[PDB]
Amino acid sequence: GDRLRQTENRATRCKVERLQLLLQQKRLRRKARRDA
Amino acid sequence: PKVPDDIYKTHLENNRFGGSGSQVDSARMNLASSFVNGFVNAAFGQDKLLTDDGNKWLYKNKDHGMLSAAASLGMILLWDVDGGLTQIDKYLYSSEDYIKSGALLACGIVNSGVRNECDPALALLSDYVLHNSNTMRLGSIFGLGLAYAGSNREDVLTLLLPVMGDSKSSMEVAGVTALACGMIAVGSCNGDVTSTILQTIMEKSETELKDTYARWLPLGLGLNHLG
């Protein structure tokens, strides 16, 4: 119950962090392409 | 941003019962306010109720009203996948299953209508598809369906389909999964989706089919075969 919820919260945190990183990379790549 | 009061314009109306007026369901009216705020501020990204202090407004609601109010945030942040997560994360980890399900649906809504290579909707909502909480199942299924409506994504479809046949799935979850599959495979005549829906319909009893939530399975098949 509580342990499962904590594990799910950690997994979602990690996934969100990875997603934000990937999106920042995508945004900067798009900006670089537009500048080019 | 426009708050619901601006739309309501109560002061114009003749305030005959400005004192001890009719006692309406305050929770229901708060839910109506949340829906109105979402609709009025849809796609703009700024809101004067959830953004300034969202926890207060959310806890103002009751039961599922919290789920709908949380999804309203994604409705507001529509088409802003990049900014959707940085705002919905606060509510993605909440002590209330209703709020977490609403955050899942909000992410799905935010991704709806736009396509990224990061597949944020899948990445976030593939975890809670089979979770033991039916409310979270509902939120995740509907979010995925709205995020990938009209896409015909085989990975998402194969992820979603077992939910219909899963034992620990209420009629509500079964119907919502049928709806999500229909939206994902609209105008595709998917053999997998049609076979799964037909098997699910046949597997149930007359008493179970008397439920109104079961009306969402034929709707799923029709959406699959639309046009």
Image: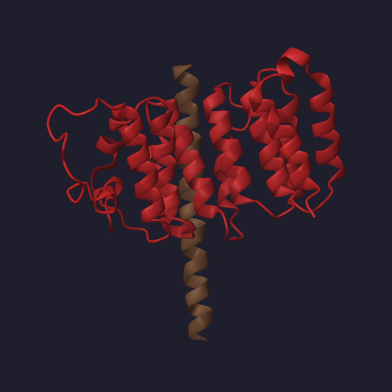
Chain colours: A brown, B red
Figure quadrant of the N terminus of chain B? bottom left
What residue appears at the point 67 percent right and 39 percent down from the top-left corner?
B179
What residue appears at the point 54 percent right and 35 percent down from the top-left corner?
B139
Q: Quadrant of residue A6?
A: top left
Figure quadrant of the C terminus of chain B? bottom right
Expressed as whole percent of the image width and height from the top left, the position of residue B100 reads 44, 33
B94 left or right of B133?
left
What residue appears at the point 14 percent right and 35 percent down from the top-left corner?
B18
Residue found at the very far bottom of the displayed protein = A36
Q: Quadrant of residue B28?
A: top left
Q: Is residue B21 above or below residue B16?
A: above
Q: How many marks?
A: 0
Expressed as whole percent of the image width and height from the top left, the position of residue A3 reads 46, 19
What residue appears at the point 54 percent right and 80 percent down from the top-left corner?
A33
B45 left or right of B11?
right
Residue B99 can be seen, yes or no? no
B124 left or right of B167?
left
Expressed as whole percent of the image width and height from the top left, the position of residue A14 reads 48, 42
Residue A30 can be seen, yes or no? yes
Expressed as whole percent of the image width and height from the top left, the position of residue B46 reads 32, 57
B29 left or right of A1?
left
Q: Nearer the viewer, residue B182 or B55?
A: B182
Residue found at the very far left of the displayed protein = B19
Q: Nearer the viewer, residue B6 or B45?
A: B6
